[PDB]
Amino acid sequence: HWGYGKHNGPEHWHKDFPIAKGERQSPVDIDTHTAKYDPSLKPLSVSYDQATSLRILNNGHAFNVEFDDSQDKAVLKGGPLDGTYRLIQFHFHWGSLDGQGSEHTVDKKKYAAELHLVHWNTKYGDFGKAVQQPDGLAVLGIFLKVGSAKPGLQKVVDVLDSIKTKGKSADFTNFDPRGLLPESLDYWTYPGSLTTPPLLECVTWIVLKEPISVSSEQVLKFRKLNFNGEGEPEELMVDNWRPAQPLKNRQIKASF
Ligand SMILES: [Zn+2]
């Protein structure tokens, strides 16, 4: 099955998912001199005051914090978006070392981790219909650099113990995602896809310019997770990041 090892790594995904070599693949390298400032681009609108987290799950390639998306409780709008996108879940991508982990790179600079807050267009009614459309999903990408601790992240850090291996889940209520956002909402945007199989090209990527810093110990716990299910040989969940894909004449626009 797909994963991130040498035998089932990102380099083999095309076999089972041909779209892997498509025209609007993610992630990509954001070249700052080449991105275009677009003044017609509106400020993002992040309204997460009413978000309802439900649980955290180790799905074998990461850990997802999932939200109640049966109503417009946590939404994202504005930016290069048209309509309302409801928050479904958030997960991360991290490395074995602080020197790598992010999916997107800036001027070829690799961050320690990358957070993805996944949202779906409500005119499609359900997440499942949404992935089938060109403007079905909106993902907020936030880079993580090692420095000072991120208070807002500790709640997550603390429950990882609980969902060590694939298939485990834990009750994860009352978690406010506002605690993971940077001060500034300046962004870069381009049309791309999911960074994991099925790699569908349904995403409008919104990657924040300003990184959030987390401490060395915060990041360390992410690395204690396992790709394997319980009672199986242990394989640390590290380097669950897909490398940069060809931009292929897509244009990266900047809000600043
Ligand atoms: Zn992701």
Image (cartoon, rainbow, N blue to C red):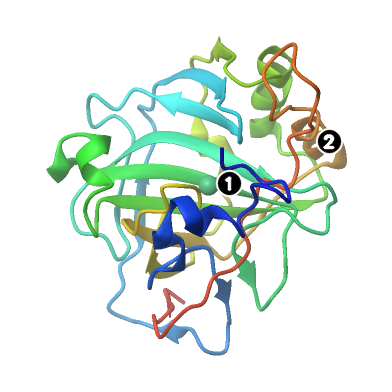
Identify the residue position indicated by label 2 in the image: 220
Instruction: Give neighbour class at mark 1: few <14, some 14-19, many 20+ (Cα, 10 Å).
Output: many
In which quadrant will I find the N terminus?
top right
What residue lies at 27% left-to-right and 78% top-to-bottom? Answer: 40
What residue lies at 22% left-to-right and 46% top-to-bottom? Answer: 84
Q: Is residue 108 above or below residue 137?
A: below
Q: Are marks 2 and 1 in contact (CB under 8 Å)?
A: no
Comparing 149 with 219, the one in front is: 219
On the rendered structure, is 28 left or right of 162?
A: left
Residue 100 is situated, as x and y percent measured from the top left of the image, at 77, 58
Mark 2 vs ligand 1: CB under 8 Å? no
**What element does badge 2 sit on?**
helix
Comparing 51 with 202, the one in front is: 202
Instruction: Give neighbour class at mark 2: few <14, some 14-19, many 20+ (Cα, 10 Å).
Output: some
Residue 157 is situated, as x and y percent measured from the top left of the image, at 71, 26
What residue lies at 61% left-to-right and 34% top-to-bottom? Answer: 62
**What element does badge 1 sit on?**
strand
What residue lies at 13% left-to-right and 44% top-to-bottom? Answer: 123
Q: Is residue 167 above or below residue 254?
A: above
On the rendered structure, is 164 left or right of 233?
A: left
Mark 1 vs ligand 1: CB under 8 Å? no
Residue 168 is situated, as x and y percent measured from the top left of the image, at 59, 14
Comparing 199 with 223, the one in front is: 199
Identify the residue position indicated by label 1 in the image: 115
Q: Is residue 199 above or below residue 70?
A: below
Distance of label 2 from label 1 (alpha carbons) = 16 Å
Amino acid type of the residue that numbered disc 2 sits on in the rendered structure: Leu
Point out which mark residue 142 bears. none
Amino acid type of the residue that numbered disc 1 sits on in the rendered structure: Leu
